[PDB]
Image (cartoon, rainbow over all chains, first blue to last red; front, side):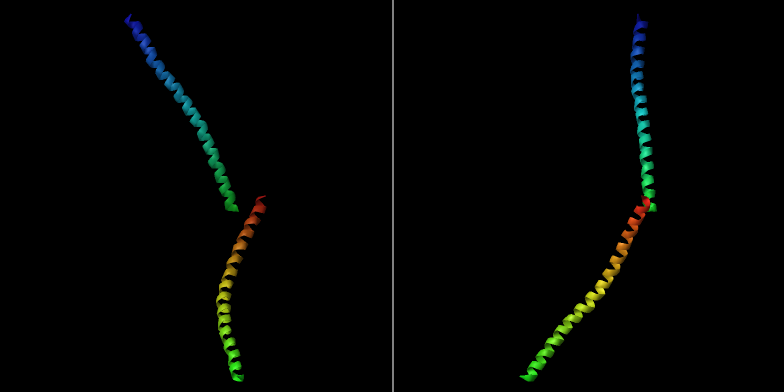
Length: 55
Length: 56
């Protein structure tokens, strides 16, 4: 049936979108951890700079 | 001969005197400046290590 063709094509396109979405959310959470590391890094940098200041 | 040697001594004296005074004045003033430069330098580094000790 034409409805089955529409059904399968709908699942195909939406599933491609879902897979891309899954990779996208994974990318974002990876970036979340990266930004956390970034924040910690600069925090430590600031600490060292303050140590230098007192020095 | 006698006065020839007298003035030989005098010429040597005065010649080397001009040399020595040049040496003296120029390098003394220079070294005085160098001394104060080294003074401030070493004092700064001394305090640097002082702060390092307090950092410990």
